[PDB]
Image 1 (cartoon, rainbow, N blue to C red):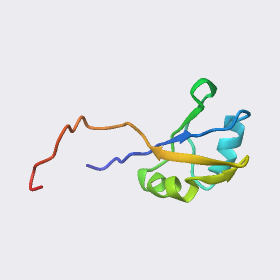
Image 2 (tube, rainbow, N blue to C red; image 1 turned 180 degrees about the vertical axis):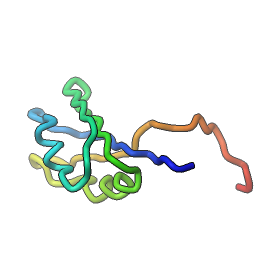
Image 3 (cartoon, rainbow, N blue to C red; image 1 turned 120 degrees about the vertical axis):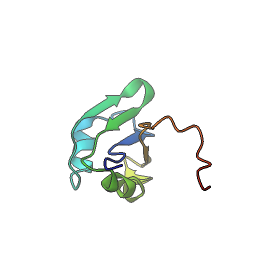
Image 4 (cartoon, rainbow, N blue to C red; image 1 turned 30 degrees about the vertical axis):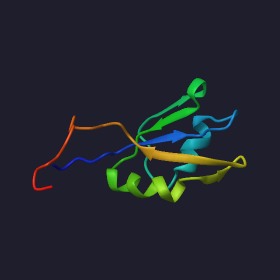
Amino acid sequence: GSSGSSGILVKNLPQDSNCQEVHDLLKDYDLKYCYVDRNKRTAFVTLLNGEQAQNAIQMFHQYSFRGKDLIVQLQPTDALLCSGPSSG
């Protein structure tokens, strides 16, 4: 277990939402790829490391953008872990 969840989901996007805007927004962090989906108003961003996201999420969560509250969440990237009773 070394690699982490390096990525975040950009939900609650405006009507004129675009990557050029997102990229600049997450300037502090290093972006690898960006996929804006107007149809579903969702932009998938791939940060450098996971730790960065864990923070960038809330740090940018409900952020001020076009009078809207940009909702940032974690990526689906999961290890198919239905449950985890192991010493739970």
